[PDB]
Length: 401
Ligand code: HEM
Image 1 (cartoon, helix red, strand yellow):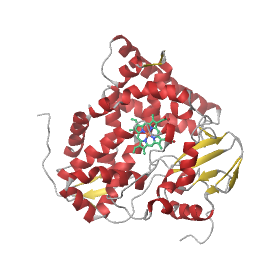
Image 2: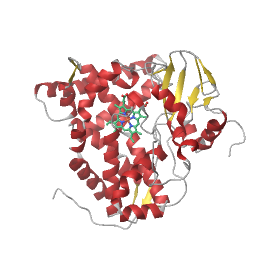
Image 3: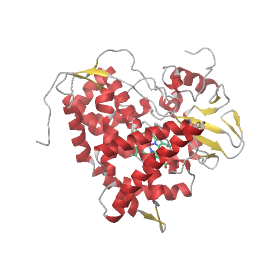
Image 4: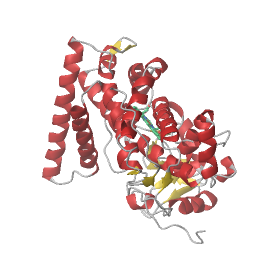
């Protein structure tokens, strides 16, 4: 609908929250596929441009850091191969198909307890009460920590992210260092405990992981854990809430899923495409190149706009329709290539198990009202801030009795 070129700052969180992004993306894909925003920041907005960049890390490097407004960090997403590959193989010990599928019972049980807390009410905030608690509880359990310790880790990772985005004065630098120290010392205390007396938790697995004769240091484990805390929490939340929102807005598709649970995996893929919780990841050019009509220079960052790519008309045909039967559905919500989301199968499992139970226990779930759901103004990961819903009450399972 945009008749004029978007005049936007792609580092401004409100761009991703005010609802104007998809029509801005439409203009970019049609007119200026590798777009430069009002500060000259380049962005790959078509599916082909995103995929080309992903397939060519030699040219589009991750070592400059994957944010535009934070320094590079010592975890795997800010590495190139071969370093990245080694680190990923080490951490992958925690995410084998065996270990993910072993979480089916615990995640299912977790989902039942969350729904138990709301089922008698006839209403809840789908974000606050269902979508937000689940991913963090799953990560907490995976790490083998107590709920109280989970919550400390959550607060620390929140403060670290905040600090990393702005530590200009002398004091924010120290608060940032204090927070890093607090988080590092807590996590290393846990690591030290598992080094002596191992469990089956993710800390123990990372401690024991060995690849090409190398093992992870305590600090490496601390930072890969931090990446998992950040990367696996709000992302999963936003696909759950935003994906469910679209199911609630398309009653025929909601009904189809209620009638046939085997349709759920296809539905989850469309929930992923539509929500695209990770709005962008940055790459740094290692050479000058002319890329989809734009002159890029060595050393500049470019944003890979995953939501923009996921609504590419040349690829999806009818991307502006939400359809649980979309097939094929080669969305890039999880990225593509060597950095393809390590947690993708765990995320898909959380999404499937929760939505299964929501369909079964809240079968007449509806939005309280059809107004658009408010979105988080963040330039990295974003989705619904709240989502009031209503449903016929039902009795809690209380499975531990
Ligand atoms: C809906 C949920 C999720 C989405 C949409 C998502 C999205 C992404 C994206 C876009 C990337 C970067 C890929 C690229 O640049 O090509 C990534 C990487 C990563 N994700 Fe996820 N993520 C999700 C859930 C999770 C979970 C649950 C975990 C772990 C428990 C996780 C851990 C990671 C890690 C460690 C990486 C770095 C992989 C690497 O650099 O090799 N993510 N994710």
